[PDB]
Amino acid sequence: MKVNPFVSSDSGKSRKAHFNAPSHERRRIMSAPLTKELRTKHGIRAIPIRTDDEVVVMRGRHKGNTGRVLRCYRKKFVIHIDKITREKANGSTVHIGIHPSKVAITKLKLDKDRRALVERKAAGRSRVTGIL
Amino acid sequence: APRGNQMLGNAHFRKHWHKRIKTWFDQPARKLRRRQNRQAKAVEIAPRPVAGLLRSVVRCPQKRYNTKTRLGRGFSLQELKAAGISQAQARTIGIAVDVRRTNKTAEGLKANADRLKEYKAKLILFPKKASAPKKGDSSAEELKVAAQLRGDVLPLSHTITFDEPRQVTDAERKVEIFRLLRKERADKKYRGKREKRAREAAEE
Amino acid sequence: HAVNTKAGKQHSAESWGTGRAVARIPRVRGGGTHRSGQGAFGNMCRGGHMFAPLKVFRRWHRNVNIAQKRYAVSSAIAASGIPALLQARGHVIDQVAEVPLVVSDKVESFRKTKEAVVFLRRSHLWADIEKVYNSKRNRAGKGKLRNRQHKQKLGPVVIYGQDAECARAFRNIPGVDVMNVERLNLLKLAPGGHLGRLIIWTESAFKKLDTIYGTTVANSSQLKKGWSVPLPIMANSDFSRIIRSEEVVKAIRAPKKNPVLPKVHRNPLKKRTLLYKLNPYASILRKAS
RNA sequence: UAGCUUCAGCGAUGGAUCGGUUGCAUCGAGUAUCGAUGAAGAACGCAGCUUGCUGCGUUACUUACCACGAAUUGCAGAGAGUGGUGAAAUUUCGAACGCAUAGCACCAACUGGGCCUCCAGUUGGUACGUCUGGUUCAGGGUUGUU
RNA sequence: CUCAACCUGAACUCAGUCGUGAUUACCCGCUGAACUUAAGCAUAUCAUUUAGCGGAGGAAAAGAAACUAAAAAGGAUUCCCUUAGUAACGGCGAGUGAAACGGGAAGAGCCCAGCGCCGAAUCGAUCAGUCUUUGGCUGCUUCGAAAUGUGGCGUAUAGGUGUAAGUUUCCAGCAGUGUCGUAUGUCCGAAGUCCUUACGAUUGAGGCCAUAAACCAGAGAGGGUGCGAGCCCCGUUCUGGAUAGCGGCACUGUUGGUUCGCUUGCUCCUUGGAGUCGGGUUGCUUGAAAGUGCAGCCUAAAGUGGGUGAUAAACUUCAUCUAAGGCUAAAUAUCGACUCGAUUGCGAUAGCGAACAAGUACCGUGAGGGAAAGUUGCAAAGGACUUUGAAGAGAGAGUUCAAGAGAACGUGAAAUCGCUGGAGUGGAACCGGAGACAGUUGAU
RNA sequence: ACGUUUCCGACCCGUCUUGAAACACGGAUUGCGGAGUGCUUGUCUACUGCGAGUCAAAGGGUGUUAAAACCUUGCGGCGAA
RNA sequence: CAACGUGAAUGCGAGGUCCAAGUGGGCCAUUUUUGGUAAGCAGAACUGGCGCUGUGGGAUGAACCAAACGUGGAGUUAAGGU
RNA sequence: GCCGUUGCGACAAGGUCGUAACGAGUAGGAAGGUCGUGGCGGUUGCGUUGAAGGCUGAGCGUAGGCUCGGCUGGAGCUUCCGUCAGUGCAGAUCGUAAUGGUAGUAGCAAAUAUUCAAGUUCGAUCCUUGAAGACUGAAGUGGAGAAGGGUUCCACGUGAACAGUAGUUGGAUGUGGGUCAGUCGAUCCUAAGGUACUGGCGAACGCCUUGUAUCAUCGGUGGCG
RNA sequence: UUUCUAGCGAAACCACAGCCAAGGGAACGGGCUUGGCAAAAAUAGCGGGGAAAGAAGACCCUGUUGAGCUUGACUCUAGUUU
């Protein structure tokens, strides 16, 4: 149970915040878990997903498929993955949106900022796990 | 249309009372707010007592209450002089001063003088500048014991005592109490008429 | 809770009167919108004020006698010591060692829900927590929409005497409450107003019980000025024992049956045997005839 | 036979009911911050395509700076974009201020018309009341001096 | 008559300021109804209230006794409980109606005029230095305000002189040192998407060494994810950590200013608000009753004087304050504004008028009036292509768990209506009781 | 059994009214909404606790599943003349 | 205080207190009866009815005759009839 | 015979049973309701292998209503114990939304009037061209303006809605285009009148006077410069 | 015009419905009792009935309901005279 008097356990408030969150907050909301191997490799559990990452679908009708994430449609709270597509009536091809919480990251797109973020998360995890 | 045996109605609801309505849904909130204010004041003025100034001992005005005592606004100038404290010293030491109250009886003056003396005995005075203590200033191991007092300073005691059993005396038994009371009433009632009769006799 | 004092009364509505072939309800004024000419104000009208709008100054809270509160708390505590009442209230106490269940003061030293769960499981109180887990469900009705999404069973209540911050070990276990013996809550001792909550007493709380609630001697309580355990109006509360006691058996008279009535009136004038049974001389008279 | 009524099955018209819910109602808590440095409100305008709503003000669905760190998305398109926000900017009416109140006019400089007494443009200024001080004054109102 | 002062009054696009207009929940001053009740109605009541006008703040106002009272007395203001539906008012009808004492929240005291002493010791602009410069400190700067008196002492507890004792600093800034708060930003966090099964999709069911066991739990609040999730994600717990900023404190340093005071005893001197109070009358107002409060007109003071002590007046015992000048936080009110947390409230005819391009569409010249309107699907995958038609549209087909979920799309009631089959059918039809027929259903 | 056919019975409900099937009024049909309530004050009654007492107010102390619960009254209300 | 003991018929349990609803337009009939020429008119007395009430009969009817009512069956009747 | 009420009674039970008599009812009063509805504190369970909701056969109960079956539907629902209530509709010329018979009915009849051939079109009484016949008849059914309207103006497309028949046409609808001033007006002057300043009044927002009420209200030639 | 046709297409009203005689009844029935009777579906007229529709009688009365107006009604008042 929450103890912070300034954190609301109101379902309506939670839903309103979730569905009106700005882009930078939707970035945090659209987080995906690392696979077991990558988790042991990097020391972190989950990270805000990013374009050009590599993931594997863990649930749904496309479970088991792998590919690179093309777009993070934050407005629609979904990510488009490479090769995860269907055909419209006319024949054109459309990517199927997948919620990042239902995939697992297999490889991180790392740059200066992403490396710094992963280092921060790993250090914090080490600290808290040592304390626990 | 009241019917049968009833108590005649008396409700005062003929005004537009819906415009003036007061609810008490914030009573616990007000309680918590006042507790928080007391805590903040205690932190601000520590180690001084939270209650604030010391108050005097008083007798309730009317004869319906004059057998009781309660806390007063402060100490009279006569009381301060008897206890050997200046008004300015009392102000800086944290003693309430009642500039309006005046003493007309030795017992009432002495009760508050004793209260002031006891407070002065219990008082702990910190150095004005911590480095250099002065005269009248409390000692270091005394200052180490200083703690904030909560509630009224020198709270009064409202316990009732019973007089010790004694022997009934013949002088006590021989008095006519009812006749004495009636005699006092008659004397007070007829004082003026007797004075008028005496004046008329003197003129004659 | 209350409705807005001006709800349904924000229209400059007037009645059309008679002669217009419509009901005399007040109607919205103006034109050019569908609202114009529609009924207003009345509780029968769409958009009007409800009947007797609920007011905010209703009698929400109650004054409860302190003596009756203490009586209720004591009765709940006493009922917690009856295994049958716990089963009736639905607690699983099949393998519980004893009722009341007193436990060593070490439980007050717990700091981890792992420790608490191990203690419960070894004490055989995990059946109640599993029943709570199975009992969690969706609440039926509008309560779901009002931050009351789920309904689930209540588990045991651990009562401690000297808090070594032991409640932390128990907070996260569903259905398990924690209380301090000094301030015992009737709302948690008898949830739903029903007797027989399952209580885990620590040694300190069990020892302090007498100090707090006193005994049957008047003014025996020290932390409740003038309070003492109430006396019963019936000494022996089992109705069959008195009935079958030797004194009552001696006084009682032997049981009887329902009185028997003839029920059916037959026709001796038409029959022979009945008439002769009632009047044997009739047979002699007929013989003479 | 048809029509009418009725029963069973099927289908229309209609939008009741049920199922939640970024909405509403009430209770409680914390804070004190509008305006001539131009408020509240109104009008008009601003987007590559965008009427309305929302946002913004001629730097006009926003500039700068700082934090985070890869998007926006309907189609295009090319330290993103979000959040904070201390720098800069903030149209016209409006207490609304040159006078009037949907119009016209005065002062100064500078620039252009070739010159300029005449035009045009830009900039700055010209409201009512009031306080303090300044300058120039009026009155046999009182007084002194020639 | 010349010149020079003062007084009074002007003009300035003179130098520098200030006011106006908004907001309504609370606050302060005015103005001020009627409906209604009295079973009629005029006093009364509604009500010293809707409506109208003006003026502020974060609170406002009030406030340090011309008080309460009659004890062995209390001692500013504000607020709560109680006093109490009491005293009292009232066509004494209907009705109205306080306060002190008592228990508590909070508590903080002071400044003038006058008398007296110093007597311009005081102050604003401007100039020049100087600093930590949206403001401060210094002056032979130059002007001006001020003797029709600015400043210092000093105000009912008085006060002052002298004297004897004791005792003697205080403000504001800057820098540092820590100590503590922040509805202040940013960053950081424990454990299964494990096996079997179910599903369109699992979070659903079962199993995960162990006597006590999948694992975490100081985290089993909430939300999202293909209804169901502590363990998939954001989050939650850590009376959370790191970091930057704001503050408050305590101590050190340092800059500027400032301190002949302060208390108690003795001595001598000294000590106060006028068209105001009070009185008459008039009107309103109050529970205030031979006048509670306010105001108009007339009258109009005194100095142990004046006010008050609730029944008016004289003559008497006293008691208690010191009016006609001023400042002052806290406890208190209030969601109108900004930001938050909740609920035994409503669940789209309900709840705000407004869950949605709602104070919108639309209406009225205007003041103003004022709606209806939520729902495809997990995902548009929003029906390619063939075929008839000019087209709407239809017949195939495809997508989909599903389209009889196909765009006005969740569900899809009743009224009403069309078709197919059966049966009845002479100016009503429906209905209760009792059979028959058709039909339905049961038989170890 | 809201199907058909027979025999008997069979006037349209609500309302005011002495009297309604009425040539008395409302009602074309269906869905949804729709009316003895809240509070203050009395009285009686039922139940519960204590009992010459009882209830305690504002308030204070505590309480973090903290608007709850728990503790707390020279004094106050009602009662005891 | 001492004695005496239930003194007409028939039927039958009796008494007390509190709280409160609706009503406060009535109408009809045998007999008596006032006003009126009379009235299905107006006003009274006793009792019974309708109002509040269905049922058999009077072809029909608020009041007339019979008789008052749970839901069914058998038998017998009332008024009335064949 | 059965149901229930009343009285009495038996039984170790807020219950069962026995027994005798009884059973009208408006206004009204009580009692029972495992009759029904929505919450809360608890308790008992069901659910994408199908909840609520909806339609409707086998039964149960004197009744209020309830259980089950079949179909539709797609996410919630429920037993029992206490307690609470925005708790039950046939009416109120009730509110609101929708729908019938009337009924393919009343009706679409003032302003003289149209016809022929052709064009376009899937399609022409109604659009266009030509020919004919009529009408307004210059105080017009003509040509232009003021107020008002605000794009209705012009061109090209048009399928639905609208044009109370129709429509290929349109003041409709979609996409574009269009208003050029030294001389035409406004702009300038004042009329009736309005509204400011002072002044007075007013508790106040502000009002009254446009007047010797108020009033120190300026500007013109020239010289000098 | 109506009429018939093509196209288009309302409203009032509606407890349920529509043949009569007499009876009795709220004293003038479409329904009730006894009789007369009683055969689809319709078109054009019609104004006897539906005590037909329009409107909570504008006539009369009641209400301790109003309003306009008047005065020798009660109580006040601007203004004016002293």
Image (spheres, coloured by chain):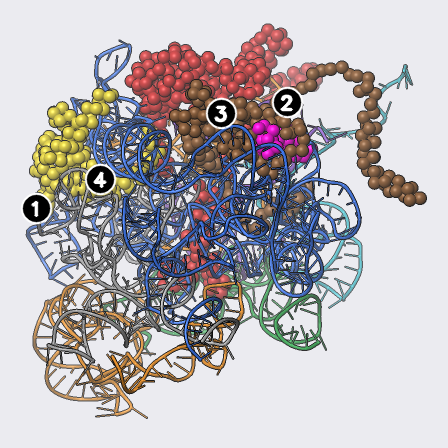
Chain colours: A yellow, B brown, C red, E blue, F purple, G cyan, H orange, I green
Q: Name the spot of residue E255 as percent of width and height, x first.
A: 32, 39
Classify mark 1: helix, strand or loop: loop
Between the residue at mark 1 and the residue at mark 2, the CA separation in whole angstroms equals: 99 Å
Chain hosting mark 1: A
Between the residue at mark 2 and the residue at mark 3, the CA separation in whole angstroms equals: 38 Å
Q: Quadrant of the N terminus of chain C?
A: top left
Q: Which residues are magenta?
A: B58-84
Same chain letter for marks 3 and 4: no
Which label sits on residue B160?
2
Residue type indicated by callout 4:
Glu
Q: Is residue A17 visible?
A: yes
Q: Which residue is mark 3?
A: B136
Q: Nearer the viewer, residue A60 or B88?
A: B88
Q: Which residue is mark 1?
A: A92
Residue type indicated by callout 1:
Ser
Q: Nearer the viewer, residue B176 or I78?
A: B176
